[PDB]
Image 1 (cartoon, helix red, strand yellow):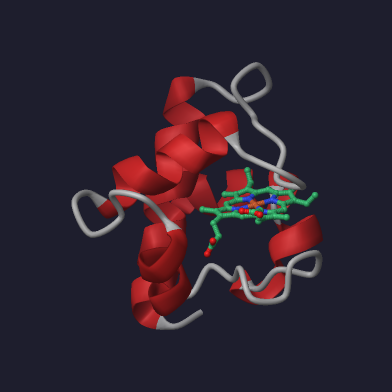
Image 2: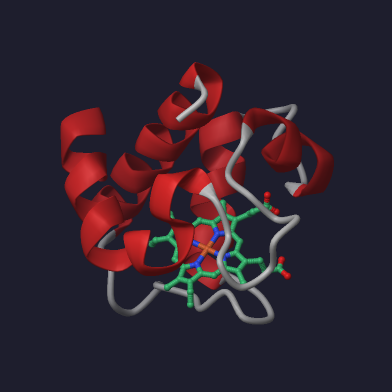
Length: 88
Ligand code: HEC
């Protein structure tokens, strides 16, 4: 689950979120704080909130709804939440 999410992450996310940052929008990192400050519902269900932004995305953040499977999405989400909580 988290090991799978790691692979989905480096194959589809590392390009912009290397080390849990945000090369495009500097202040929109994948840190615990940022995910809390900007991700709706994050403080309700962390993985679900991340899985949401991943499926739909916004602005410069592309959606993966057609490219990734629901399973691959829940996996990268758990991985991200895991990394945020651990500090990357
Ligand atoms: C570069 C083109 C990106 C790729 C490919 C992915 N993401 Fe992204 N992400 C990007 C931007 C420009 C932004 C911010 C957009 C905005 O204005 O809101 C984001 C944001 C996120 C977030 C929330 C970050 C925060 O506000 O703290 C999440 C949860 C996120 N991105 C996850 C993520 C994952 C798992 C990806 C791989 C499938 C991924 N992103 C790819 C730009 C880019």
